[PDB]
Image 1 (cartoon, rainbow, N blue to C red):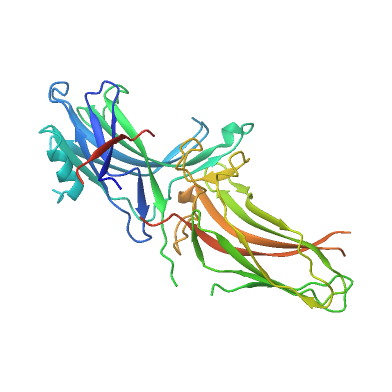
Image 2: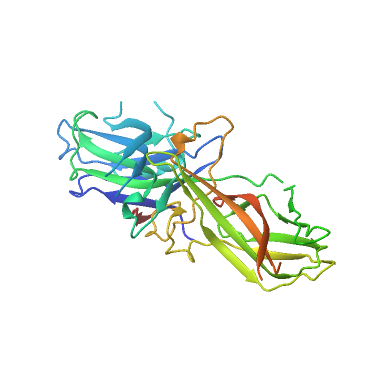
Length: 345
């Protein structure tokens, strides 16, 4: 239940506040939910000093050791210098004061989504990510040097969403182990797109024509993360794992459907892992697979996350391994009065 929640976060001196409809904004491949906000000022404090809002999207790396704005947009909510104005904006600006003015941002569809790479605590400096910060300040011109005091910043996320477009084709392998015939293996995934929490199922089909036998099958979801800026580097990492002692006898056919569901919740103390937020905030999940809009500069994306499901067989040969991986997309789930909460982030 409930009715419409608004997030607020006022600058230190409190003589400036900012209200947003939400903390995360969904990217729909072609269109990104707009950033519609309100900003409570105070004519007193603001003599001839105006109030601007900025939406910056920048890749960082360090703790700083490197930054890079992939995108920046500014507005001067006040003094109100077109725009048709949001539904919530109005509704809000009214029940707020005469000293409330709106600000609106549209985020370019091809921007990298919010993602941060948790590393360390040893390699603490090799940590990075792509963040979105909405900043509202009291300056005379948006070229001036900012004051922590009379300025507030909100770290909002761009989350990637992809509607289920209802193969996905299976993957195959066939090997020989001092055998006359192969150990033809092949699995496939149910959906082609899975959301966070949504559970993956892999149909494993084994046609062992070998005289050898499979001692066990290990199913896992691996998160491959690639850093593309400031420090090229590869990150493999299992985030799901089912080790079943199911066996496949000689000249026999196996076939079973395993089910894995990758939760950050488990892997909370992993080496290099891609999250879609800070490991602190209990709304952070494993970064979503990044969209590779055919013909797009990947460097500009900072981190390229992708997931695959690996099905490994442990034949006796004592111990030999046969397997195949299955690619798949991991997306972010699809979406009275007021009720104020602290942005807190």
